[PDB]
Image: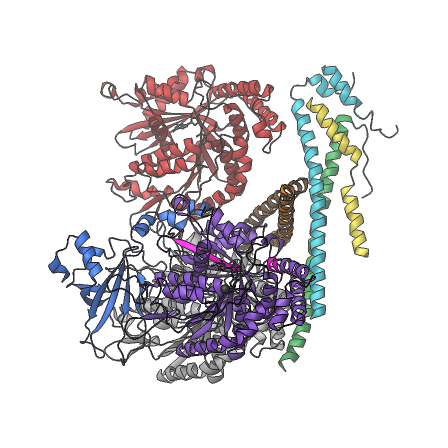
Chain colours: A cyan, B yellow, C green, D purple, E blue, G red, H brown, I orange
Amino acid sequence: KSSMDAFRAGQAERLKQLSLASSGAMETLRGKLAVAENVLKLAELARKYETEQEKVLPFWNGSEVDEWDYLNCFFRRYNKAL
Amino acid sequence: RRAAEREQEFWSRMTHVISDKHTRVWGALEKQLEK
Amino acid sequence: KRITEQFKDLQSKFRHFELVDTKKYKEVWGMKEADVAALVRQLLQADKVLHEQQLGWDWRPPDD
Amino acid sequence: REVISIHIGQAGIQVGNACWELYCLEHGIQPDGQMPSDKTIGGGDDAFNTFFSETGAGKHVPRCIFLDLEPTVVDEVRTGTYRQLFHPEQLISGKEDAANNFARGHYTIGKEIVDLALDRIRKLADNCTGLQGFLVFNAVGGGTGSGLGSLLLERLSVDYGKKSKLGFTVYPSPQVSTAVVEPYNSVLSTHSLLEHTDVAVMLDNEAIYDICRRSLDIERPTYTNLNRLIAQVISSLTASLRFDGALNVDITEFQTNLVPYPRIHFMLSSYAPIISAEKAYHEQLSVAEITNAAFEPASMMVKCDPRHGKYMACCLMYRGDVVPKDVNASVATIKTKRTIQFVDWCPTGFKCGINYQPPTVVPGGDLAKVQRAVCMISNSTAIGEIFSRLDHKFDLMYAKRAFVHWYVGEGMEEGEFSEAREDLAALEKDFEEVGA
Amino acid sequence: VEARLGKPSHLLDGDRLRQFLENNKKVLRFWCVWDERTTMYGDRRPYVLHYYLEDDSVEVLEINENNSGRDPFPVFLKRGPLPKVAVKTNTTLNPKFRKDQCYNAGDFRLGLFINVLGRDFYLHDADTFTKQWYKDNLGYTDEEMS
Amino acid sequence: MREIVHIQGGQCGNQIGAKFWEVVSDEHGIDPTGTYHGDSDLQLERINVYFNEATGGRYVPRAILMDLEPGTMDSVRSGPYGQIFRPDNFVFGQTGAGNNWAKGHYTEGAELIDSVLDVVRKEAESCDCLQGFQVCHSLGGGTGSGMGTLLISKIREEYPDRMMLTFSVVPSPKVSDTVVEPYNATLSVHQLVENADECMVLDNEALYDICFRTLKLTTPTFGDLNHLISAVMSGITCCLRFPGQLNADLRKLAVNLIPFPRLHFFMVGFTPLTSRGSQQYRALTVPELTQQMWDAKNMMCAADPRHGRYLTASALFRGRMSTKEVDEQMLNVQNKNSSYFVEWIPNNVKSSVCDIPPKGLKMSATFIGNSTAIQEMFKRVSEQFTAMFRRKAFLHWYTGEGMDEMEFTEAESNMNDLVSEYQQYQ
Amino acid sequence: MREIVHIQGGQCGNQIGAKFWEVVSDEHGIDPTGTYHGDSDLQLERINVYFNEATGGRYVPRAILMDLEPGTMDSVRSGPYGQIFRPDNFVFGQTGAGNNWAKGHYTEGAELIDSVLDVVRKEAESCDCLQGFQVCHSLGGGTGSGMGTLLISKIREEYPDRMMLTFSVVPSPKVSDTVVEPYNATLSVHQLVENADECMVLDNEALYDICFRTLKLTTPTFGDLNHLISAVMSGITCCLRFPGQLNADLRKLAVNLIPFPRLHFFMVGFTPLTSRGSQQYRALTVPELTQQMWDAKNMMCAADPRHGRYLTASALFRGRMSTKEVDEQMLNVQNKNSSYFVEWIPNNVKSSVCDIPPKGLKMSATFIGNSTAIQEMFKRVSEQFTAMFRRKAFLHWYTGEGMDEMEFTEAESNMNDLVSEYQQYQ
Amino acid sequence: FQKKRRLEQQLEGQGKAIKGLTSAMGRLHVDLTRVNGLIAANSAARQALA
Amino acid sequence: AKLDETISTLKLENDMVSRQVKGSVEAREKALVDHDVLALEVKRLRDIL
Ligand SMILES: Nc1nc2c(ncn2[C@@H]2O[C@H](COP(=O)(O)OP(=O)(O)OP(=O)(O)O)[C@@H](O)[C@H]2O)c(=O)[nH]1
Ligand SMILES: Nc1nc2c(ncn2[C@@H]2O[C@H](COP(=O)(O)OP(=O)(O)O)[C@@H](O)[C@H]2O)c(=O)[nH]1
Ligand SMILES: Nc1nc2c(ncn2[C@@H]2O[C@H](COP(=O)(O)OP(=O)(O)O)[C@@H](O)[C@H]2O)c(=O)[nH]1
Ligand SMILES: [Mg+2]
């Protein structure tokens, strides 16, 4: 009976800990996804007032990508609008 | 033991597949595109 | 006599809970790892479109 | 289903003087011994069986004895307004005082009167048929109540044994005091009270003074008000036997639900609603607020903070129009409340009882008539805190051997002083151990 | 709704405390005789009846004679409002008896018959306090109270 | 013909039984005087099951009061329909249990059990065809749990071939009335698994919230509380006392309800239940009755059935109805929520019908379920037991009369066995 | 057979439904005690679409009142015919929406919609054939908008294939009772443009104008306006409850009126609406009713049709008339006002007749038009929204409760593209 | 005071988490019932079509 | 004296809230497990569909 109770308690504890850790991870990933979809929609929102000129050419008339110059194209579009 | 550590690396992979660099990019792009 | 079968019935009961509990934990883990795989696939899809449309110039999948 | 009451010492006799007038007002008995011919309030015949036994043709007598060596208070009772109520043989009056000396009250004059007292109690119990328990009333801070009370308790225990013993004991206050040898008398009485009395109900004086100042708004109270409200608490406790209700107890549920350990029996008392006649008609009275009122530290009858301790068990008697619902709801709320904490020995530590009889108020009293009331008796470790506080002053006074010459001249010695000291110390040890 | 959100149960119905304050300790006592000698065993028997003016409730007590064949039972009927009438009972909820359905203090006339739960009591005496109360309040003459 | 002998043990048991006898006497149509005043002959032809005619139609209930409280005696005598019981049957002690299972089962029992047994033997031989025993009692008291259990053991020894219904209220921590409830429970439930044939488990909190939302009562006193229990008890013998299209006695109910000898812990419910203010607005029909009965909030136990699976269930219907709709609705409530049943027992539900609805209504039903969810409540009380036993608290009062620790540990062992086998069959 | 569940939201919707239930009950000839006292037997063959028989002639409506204040419930029960509703259907909050859409859709919804959804689920299961739901509410208040939109979203989700009639009264600047009317209306329509299937758009300004000009009442209260709305909201569904020479139910009306899956905002009107002084001095013939039906001043909305074009228009005639006469009248209207009708759809008018007119009158008519002029109100409210939202006025009361900034921008995006879609097909 | 406010805010956060979980419980129960009903319907359809 | 009384009451309130939060933790875990088991049941049922 002692062995049975110990085994059952261990199984319950492992299930509980896996559930808690997985729920935390899933909440983190859901939070990651929430920001992403807001970015996609708001990009769709501003495109309504765009002219088809910049709708067709939003950028202009081989290493990896750094985090400082990372938004140059968007800044070009913003400067065009301004 | 082995299963526990396996799950640990699995969770680390599935929660750091995307970079904090990309998270900061997403936030900054959201602000810039709002303005 | 009564506690003799209770002893063996406990053995049969112990065998039963071993099978049921082990399979239940496996099934829920498989379920939720499939779910998190679907969610991370969705996230990877979301990352690709933001780069490709706004400012990417390149995009690169991970290993797995 | 009768119980027998014995009162020893000045405080005990005065408290009983209040209790018996309260009882006769409850049961409609005139102060001259019989119920009237026209006015009939008796809710049920034989309802007085617990306390009064009819004698022949309409003359009720109490199941109580008053005894004390000082004759002044006893003859005051004899010449008072309740002359015909008592049987002239229960009133035992000595010749000379105990004079704050436990040794004097227990050894010299003790041997003389205890035999007569127990002989009278034996006849009383033999006349009784369904004897339930003993109700002793005394204060250990004096000489008579300590010595004679302890000796009589020991002899009654060795005589009967199995019956329950409820001792409503008045103890010295941390600041309020009227005598000097009270630490000595209290510890000497306690050494035997602990191992004879089944359930000791704590009572203080300063706590009740503060209660009647805060609620009844009387700035300068006397002993009469104290005894009146103590009598009200006793009546609320015995109403379960006296009257009929939807969920009742008797003297045995107390010793069953309230004593987890053979040497841990020290009960905190509380009563609600203590409300004056001015605010009675303006304030809203019901089970939720009376139950909440019965738990604040400023509403218990002994000066000790319940917050420092953790409850063991609580017993709640309800009087009047009370239904099981609102009491269960108040119980759930008080359990989920955090400002009070229960210990893990007993996850289910509430014993509730309900009785249909509303509380009564004596004519000219300081309590207004109300629809319902609640009385609480609880277990905690603040009692052990009180014991440690008293023992500190005991040892500090004893270190200089003060006042010991009276005891040694009476005939006793320092051996039992040492024994009482170590016994009390072991008692605080037991409380602090059980509190874990 | 107020009971749902927390509200005193007695204050839900209300109009209770005035009557208790006005008559906290007023009881009318009547000496009834029940005649059932027409049944097979037992004989006619006296009982007492208390009517509490605090709640308008009725409680019937039984008086025992020495060397009688009856088990000593102090109470004969629990303290409650007497229905005074037949009501179609429900298996789920017991009937709630209201004041106009139950008896009133003016119903007892010292010479009528009371249908207490089928039993047909005949009350024949009353205390002097009850007689004085009746004369004061119901304007009853001295002859009726005889 | 078939005779159910009814015993009332303890304060709770006596007070519930008083209302039960009130309900059954009202159903069979006798005024509290004890004389027959019913209108239809359907009430007379089966009056022998519960009542005995002595002389002059002065019917006397076949009930056995067993306690230690003259106060409860006065209460029973004072309550309406309280004088019908026999003064000979008023077997009562004088001391008082004082809320102690040891006192109720060993000390005072040793002297009063002889009297209770020879009285019960007296009515047992008075009746011609004994059908079974029913005892109404609590589980947390002393004179209700211990004395009733000892009576059960003696009766099982005397008559090994009779069905036994024990109507026992089991405590909950949320509504707690005394302190030694885990001890009293563990002892009584330890004995009832071997002795009692089946037990209808009940509790106070379930009845409380039932009269909260179903009946919409404001001040639900015990007079309101015990009424539902009495209604269920009266309903469980509808087939015995009245004609129907599918008869079912206690043994027939048990055989269809007990797959293994130690699974006889049934949770009960009643339909229809509705407030007084909405009676005229609500329809009366079998689908509505079924939907009301199969809900968890209509159950009289603090055990949520959605936390387990029903091993088996039974329905006792009353009133002129349709067997085809009854069967179709049982099929629906077995098929739609199939996950909450057990897969290796086909036809989990047994249904039966009677021709007479209770007075004051037109169509009724009683639900009885052997479902595995009661292991939650047993786990709860077992935890209460262990927490107090972990340093032997409140235990000197028990050991002061002859109790030991071996039986205390055996009770916990058996409770662990029951909960283990329920979780095994989940 | 076919069934319409009814739901009332907020004070405005609750009072409108309270008047509507009186109107329909009188039309079906039932006593306000729930009993039948009418004469024409044709009333009771189709009362099951709206009523359930409880016990011997007692009928209860198939409606659910929902709000967050007790005053509305007290008023509706104090009013006449308030004793017919089932008390169990009175889902009811306690704290109040405070004219706050965040409160109505995110704070009190999360705690009360679980309760209001189970009861409507039970009511829908009570009937066999579900035809649709009927939600009556406003678009300016808190609980009228937020709670209504949340409930309709849940109902659409759980019944994906059922019709939804939402009677929405919209705010107007000339008749404004609160200050955040655009903030509420835009957010509510943001969900109504996907979830609802047909929104009857109404406003109090047109009702006041009708009561002043053609009705010529001196001091009209809310009761007269609610009674005036009751006429159309009852005549819309007469085709279900009464026979007709050419029947047309809700889905038939929808498939004819709605050309594209987004344009489901209709204006409504009733005929005749004549002052009691002039009732005797005018003739009642279908040609005469057509003029008052197509009069721009008769529309129940402050949107002038002459500033746009009609896409589709439906004519629900009540009484016995000539189908040829109706058809030729509609043909003449279409030919004369050719520019006012869209070009690429031949025969922009649907017609149908029901044999039973409302009592008292022997002839009546109801007009439902899906014209493109209704974008005037959306421009009207969107300009106000932008005016207030440029400064973020009153925006803390919503931001500090659970929504963020971009939701309002999304709502305006949807509003602007909807008016763009109307202008496109114009 | 800072500890007390932190613990309290933890408290209502956990409470709202529990309440959302209970709402999920109810939604899952409703899904269970509807899915089982469809199971029975499709089983009958399978038998008829076979 | 006033500071001491307030401080003692404040520690007691901290203990109250601490164990109340612990109870909330346990309730959240139970709700999570029940959610998991119902989800498993849902997946079995959709597999049958
Ligand atoms: N509450 C209350 N306490 C009282 C009353 N009378 C006396 N006491 C207390 O009892 C304590 C001890 O009693 P004593 O004054 O010594 O009288 P005693 O107990 O008979 O002892 P002796 O003086 O030797 O006779 C005193 O300190 C008082 O505080 C009373 O009427 N009410
Ligand atoms: N339903 C119901 N329960 C009761 C009643 N009276 C007592 N109880 C229950 O009985 C339990 C305790 O039983 P107890 O009084 O000790 O039985 P005893 O052995 O006769 O003293 C309590 O939890 C009460 O809830 C009653 O009239 N109705
Ligand atoms: N037809 C009609 N409209 C009303 C009535 N009462 C209020 N309204 C309209 O409803 C709007 C206010 O909505 P309200 O009922 O307060 O919304 P809620 O507070 O969320 O329920 C106002 O603009 C009024 O024009 C009424 O009795 N009848
Ligand atoms: Mg003295």
Q: Is residue E34 visible?
A: yes
* Residue I48 % position (x, y): 61, 54
Q: Is residue E1 visible?
A: no
Query: Which quarter of the rendering shows the C terminus of chain E?
Result: bottom left
For this orientation, the residue located farthest to the left is: E143
**Picture quarter containing residue G425?**
top right
The magenta stretch is D364-387
* Residue D62 % position (x, y): 38, 69
Q: Nearer the viewer, residue E110 or D328?
A: E110
Q: Is residue E96 above or below residue G239?
A: below
Q: Nearer the viewer, residue D40 or D56?
A: D56
Picture quarter with ligand 2:
bottom left
Q: Is residue G145 above or below residue D404?
A: above
* Residue D36 % position (x, y): 27, 64
For this orientation, the residue located farthest to the right is: A63
Q: Is residue D39 above or below residue G209?
A: below
* Left or right of residue E130, residue I1 in this image: right
Residue E144 colored magenta?
Answer: no
* Left or right of residue A32, residue D373 in this image: left
Give the residue at x 51% y 26%.
G185
Query: Which quarter of the rendering shows the N terminus of chain E?
Result: top left
**Picture quarter containing residue G89?**
top left
* Residue D116 % position (x, y): 46, 77
* Left or right of residue C13, residue C44 in this image: right
Q: Nearer the viewer, residue D97 or H3?
A: D97
Q: Is residue G122 above or below residue G261?
A: below
Q: Nearer the viewer, residue G322 or G55?
A: G55
